[PDB]
Length: 425
Length: 105
Image 1 (cartoon, each protein chain N blue to C red):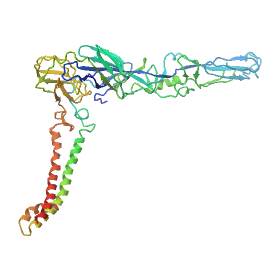
Image 2: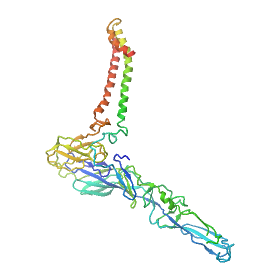
Image 3: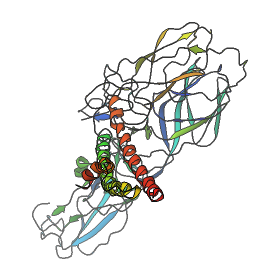
Image 4: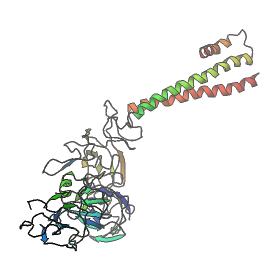
């Protein structure tokens, strides 16, 4: 009744048969449409381009002054003896103790409503498996971690845990432009020598760690303030970027920004278990088949996933058996065979089958052919492992086997013959 | 870029990326040895050239074993008819002896 462990490969139909002796049941075909890495994440920080805002000089005539306060982050220096005038250019009668409150603080732009959010991710795994019982075709989201029962069409499925499963995400930063795999250290970036100068606790924060430095000085000219200004590193670093998370993956993974996922990562194996509601009224149909043969056509040495071959047989038993196979993959799986001849079928060749044990019901042969050495000259591609397989060349290389035997017959004779001489006389 | 049905993606401007498994209007059909091997007939990764290297080394072993044993055989060929029944003037020694002369020299 239950239990196969199928590999995760997308769009390729795995055939599982594991039912009671005598096949007359429903053959299980299962497809992975996509795998769906659903995050269980911690938000490290929000970062964005920033607008530092320096108010224009406010002076108060003569004497000292003192400053105070925070707006998000602040620096404040009160310059003194500002200006040199005494005629309404200081706006004062003093210029020896006259004071300027200069101040600067950090505000956030309008990029901050958009990119970018830093996540530590460890994803939890959801599958989007397609169940084909040969009578309906339907797909279903289900979490594949845990022991997770669902019944669909009133056939039980129990999804067993998924392990040995690739993770692209680690330290990652998700921009709206394109995801990038980048390392950082949160709440400890500042100044303008780095990308992600402002460090913010939340999306709509009021506290920011930045070390940004912009230097006011006292007016001492006929103009109106001297400034040396290092401006924002973020706008500069914006071009340079990291390196993409998208290209990161040995096999599959198209990383989608908006929900935060990776679709189609062909890794991890799903053990599956089922009670398909066997009995039924089994056994009461069971084709049998005779004269089993393999023809090979469409052998080209291009790497594609297709497969185009035929098998010749004859049937005289009218039925549907549960077909086919547990070391081979057909694209068909339901065939009412009443009579039979040549039957062309599609196969998943060079996908996850490079070998095939072809069954049509309880009956079987092993196939097939096409693997020449390096001239090229066709040969069979089955049975013994010799690496162009069974070939006139493979046999000719094997024929060293006689050499060790001839050198052994010479040793046996000489060892026995000495002992015999001493005895002889 | 070579692709043996793995997947290679190229990104060109403001257009969708295209990933390909080198799909054409051809197919395979029960290719590849049951125990792991490389795509197409081609030698690389060496798994078609490994059989050449192995077979070549094997022939040398037959010569090395034959020759070394042979030498020991020639000393027994002298010994046996001498001891058997001398063997000092008989034609009998000669039949065994021809082998022994070829072995030693």
